[PDB]
Image (cartoon, rainbow over all chains, first blue to last red; front, side, top):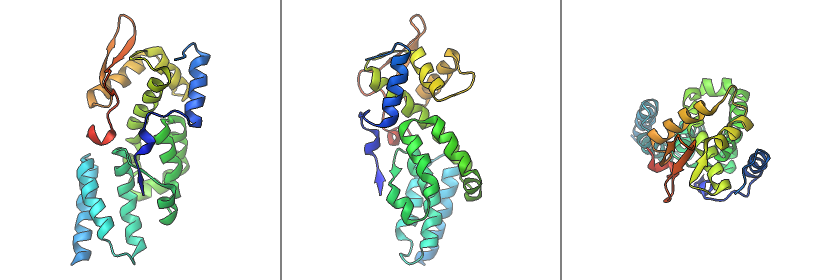
Length: 30
Length: 195
């Protein structure tokens, strides 16, 4: 019914990937 | 009556919610929801309308199944947006259903989701760069990507200062290097512990 697992430390989702591309596009990579 | 205790909890739950005591709102509204007669779906739905944003503010996202089951799919894109840190999608989803949310009496409460959405966005930046000293300009990039108009470094500082003050972010801004210095121990506490 209720989820908390959305707030783990995983960044495998689509939005995360899009933000990763945007960051790299400006010079930011891990 | 059990119907009258349920009605009582419903209203003090709303009082608490409007006074920004979300833990207490959660207690009351959860109780009302759970002890509401299984037969009356209309009752359960009305309570869920209030319990939903309260749950979300405490970091508990509803399943799409729950939302389907009570015909509250108006909350689905909002939930997805908040979960991702997707400010741009949150704004769109809120607009798409503005009237429904206002008629439900929860529009202003839903606005408070921007705060944790900011929190979620900035946590993702932290997880993507994997450093405890984060350039403020990296958060600016994320906010430009989310199309926050006129946003600049000063605005990022203001947002971060609010998040630090409220306990969402454990760290401080070092102005010499324009970095956000965050704790090495879990700088983004669970939302249910920030209350």
